[PDB]
Amino acid sequence: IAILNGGNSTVQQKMLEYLKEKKDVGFFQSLAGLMQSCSVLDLNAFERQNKAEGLGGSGEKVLQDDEFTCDLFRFLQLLCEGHNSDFQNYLRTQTGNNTTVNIIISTVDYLLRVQESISDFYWYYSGKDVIDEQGQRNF
Amino acid sequence: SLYELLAALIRGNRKNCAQFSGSLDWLISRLERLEASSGILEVLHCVLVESPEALNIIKEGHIKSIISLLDKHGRNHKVLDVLCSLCVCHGVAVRSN
Amino acid sequence: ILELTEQEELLKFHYHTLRLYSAVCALGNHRVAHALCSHVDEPQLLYAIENKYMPGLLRAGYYDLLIDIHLSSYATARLMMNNEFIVPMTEETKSITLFPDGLPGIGLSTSLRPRMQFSSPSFVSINNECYQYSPEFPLDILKAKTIQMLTEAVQEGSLHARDPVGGTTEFLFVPLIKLFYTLLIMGIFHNEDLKHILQLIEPSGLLQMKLPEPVKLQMCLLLQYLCDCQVRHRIEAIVAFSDDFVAKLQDNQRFRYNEVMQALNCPCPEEIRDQLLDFHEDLMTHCGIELDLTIRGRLLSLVEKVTYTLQQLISETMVRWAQESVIEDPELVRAMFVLLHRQYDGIGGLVRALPKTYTINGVSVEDTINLLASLGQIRSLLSVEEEKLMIRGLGDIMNNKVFYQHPNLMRALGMHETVMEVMVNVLGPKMVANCCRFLCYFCRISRQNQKAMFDHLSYLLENSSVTPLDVAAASVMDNNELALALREPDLEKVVRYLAGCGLPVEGERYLDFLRFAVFCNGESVEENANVVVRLLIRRPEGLLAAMEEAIKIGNAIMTFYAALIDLLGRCAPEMHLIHAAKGEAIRIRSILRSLIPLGDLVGVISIAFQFCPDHKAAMVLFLDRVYVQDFLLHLLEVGFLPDLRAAASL
Amino acid sequence: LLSKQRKRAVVACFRMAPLYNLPRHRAVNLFLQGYEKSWIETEEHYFEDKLIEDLAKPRVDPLH
Amino acid sequence: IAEFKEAFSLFDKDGDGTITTKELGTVMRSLGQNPTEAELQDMINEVDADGNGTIDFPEFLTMMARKM
Amino acid sequence: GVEIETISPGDGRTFPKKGQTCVVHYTGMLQNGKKFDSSRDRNKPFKFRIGKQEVIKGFEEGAAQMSLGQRAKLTCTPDVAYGATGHPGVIPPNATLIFDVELLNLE
Ligand SMILES: [Ca+2]
Ligand SMILES: [Ca+2]
């Protein structure tokens, strides 16, 4: 992200042609492989540590270190800034190699997992209605 | 040249040297043909650098053969580093041998 | 030998023999090292060192042979303990000057650095009596030769001769520096020679010369050890400062923090509970506010002093060698910048040292030496009837006086990972049970040590043989936090092993492991309880009918089902309104008792009037938690009557 | 009120009167253990932009 | 002086010379404090310096002599 | 019993008496003169008590026969020596060893 932090374009030119000449289906394969689970705020692990600290460091619950994931989708956003309409097409269809991985489909399936992860977290929470930090920080 | 072909097919995979349990003493028995042994020797050297499993296969009766291989041929340093590779595996060394 | 410089067949064949001598005596074959010196007789190697007409192949072999005959056994031994930095609290350690107003040639060096034990290479009937460490030679004569070698070779090699001994400059410099490298590590070259040898290198020139490729790679390893000795001096600097600081801070706060406690009344409103807390948290509370008393002038002075010369030129000389001399050898450039990162980040190396070290007292320095030797024994033994030394090593660890006193130290040594590596190294077996018996002893000594063993259960269960499974259940026995930290998917692998017992006996161990997985305190958890019994619908495994069939009919099946009831007896919902006034915790009360219509008088009466106290006492907890005062009277005298009759039947 | 007020001193007498009192070994250790999370995390770390700009000083550059 | 033995007997009910965490948790729930198992294991091992796990009577009496 | 050729005589009458540790100097080669040991080479005097049975018995029986200052040649029978195994790595099966032994002091 540090190279692309200004929404750079010459480097955006560089990654596309490097993906064209030395065509690497393993890269997008390793993207969705990274992207596969990658985080879920999963309230089952939330319940136990409340009971654990209720009757006995901490903080390792939250989507299993989701700070990595905030960097990954930042890297995906900074890979298509400036509306690189070739490259925005390229992340969809990827017509270089023999096989292809549509990451644009997969990134819908990330937040769909996240939306299901956050909605029931309210639905567990919808009756207690007074907020501690552990609700606030994990939100 | 046949041994030269087979010497190629071991240096790539860790599988193929691991697929050479029973051929080992078979090759050491064929080693006493004593006319084409250098082709057999590059074969048996290359398997020994790529499988730590194959080191535990070879026992003393094969070793005394290889020592007497130095007798029949005299002074061949290709034989000599085979014993050095028989000493140390990829990282480790066996105290028994 | 000097004739061989054109006898290239006999040159090369003797070279590969010289490989083979250096081959077989590797990683400390100390009996074979005593065998080889009869053929080599190291005063021959002294003549092999000095002769400036030996070929370069014979030179590099002979210098390498001199190391791994005599030195590499100790050299790798002190190479292992170069990441421990433990120290005693004695007065000479207390009275180090700690600072310049800088030299890497530190005089004191009061760390542990284990012993120098050699043995004579005699040929008398002490065969399995000396047998253990190393041959020896007058190494003090040798270090005189090296300075005689190096100072001559620098001032002669300065003019860039076309001679030098192996023809090239590579055979000239590399075996000397490598010999100097290992000899520096072994606690030789006291500071009269360090100041002499740095006059050959630093003066503050040898590194300023033009050099070939692998020689600076040797120098790269040489520079790192000076930086390493810079590090251990700083830890030895910080520990004596920790002596009087704690001696102040224990008297200053804790007595005067108690002074307002005596002058208060006895209530604990705010001021008592703020530092009366957990001990490490009390130290975290006491030290946490110093970076925002009368003592904090001592801290802020010293952090400026343990800010931190060599750091100038080392940060220069990597930039030189990259600039004019574009490099091959990816080993070298990897070796280069890790110095350069460590030079511009000296604190980050000091980060990764402080959770590795400790300070002990002078009485405990005895029991550490053999312990560090036996820990050094195992790490040497890691590279391989081979394990006969290991069990005597492991039993020596179990019978150490100062082993129980500091359970953090074995965690600080990381030795549990070392022993667990052997378990991976063994299992692709009599040393199995000698290993795990240490481990089940190892988790049980303290609390956060048991936390350290917790992080391996995903691997640990996979090798259930009959014990390895003893370790996993021992790592969860009491800590309810570690009970809650355990998750579901490994228990799928647990009950998969139970489905394999549809042929049995060996399900007796998984159920005891699950008995430690749900109860753990004197009162069960419910999160581990619900998930396993929902799996035990999916798998089935007359029950009370065939229970009496084992009473007459190899005594394992009556013990086998005796745990299965005890598993269910632990995973009751509760015995309260925790059980009663709740939701769906009573739903498991149905699905449990639905599979068991009662019939339990087989377990109650038929054994108890004669294998007795195991099955029926486990049957007690099932009726007690899962299951009116007619039954408070119905089952009576069934068990109490033989307890009354056979009481004096001893 | 008398018997329960003295008990509240015995409530706290565990947590209060032993406070790093006996062991000088654990005291000097947990100082260092406390010293790690407190004083080490500093900001001598603006060398990096000087470091990389010390690398691009030329062939192939040392950064390259 | 014997009232210190009375306060020691207020915990000890099984009668073996050691105070386990169940007794201190019992009197602590009878008073009104709701300690966690971390705090209860702390205070039940805040006496523990030898490492037997529980609270003995000599350390309790010198603790009573050390506070007041 | 075991064969001894006296190389040069010392004092004759002060043999190494039982209960003394013999500060000696020695070397050693094979039957063919293949050298394999020298206490002079390591610049170190070997020391051993008579009756302690820490040296091999042929060397002790040869050492008892000599005298103070006397140096001698110990041509030992290999079967009184290490024997059929030899030294497992040094001395071959059943080869006659030739020492040049030389006494310096006692205890
Ligand atoms: Ca008790
Ligand atoms: Ca006690």
Image (spheres, helix red, strand yellow):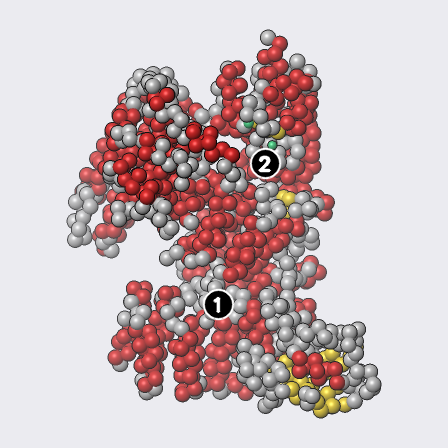
**Identity, as a three-letter code, of the amino acid under mark 1:** Arg
Residue annotated with mark 2: E51
Q: Nearer the viewer, residue C297 or B82?
A: B82
Give left or right: position of C435 versus B40.
right
* Residue C503 horizontal/vertical position (percent): 26, 48
Q: Residue at x 76, y 74 (%)?
A: F21
Circle 2 residues within 10 Å: few <14, some 14–19, many ≥20: few
SS category of the residue bearing label 2: loop
Residue C495 lies, with reference to residue F27, above or below; the image says: above
Tell me, yes or no, whether dots 1 and 2 are on the same chain: no
Q: Is residue B13 above or below residue A32?
A: below
Position of residue C150 in the picture relative to residue C413 (left or right): right
Q: Quadrant of ligand 2?
A: top right
- Pick the residue in front: A59 or F62: F62
Place residue C181 in its image quadrant: bottom right
Label 1 element class: loop
Where C203 sits versus C233, above or below? below
Q: What residue would you read off at disc 1?
A: B95
The front one of C64 and C68 is: C68
Under mark 2, the amino acid is: Gly
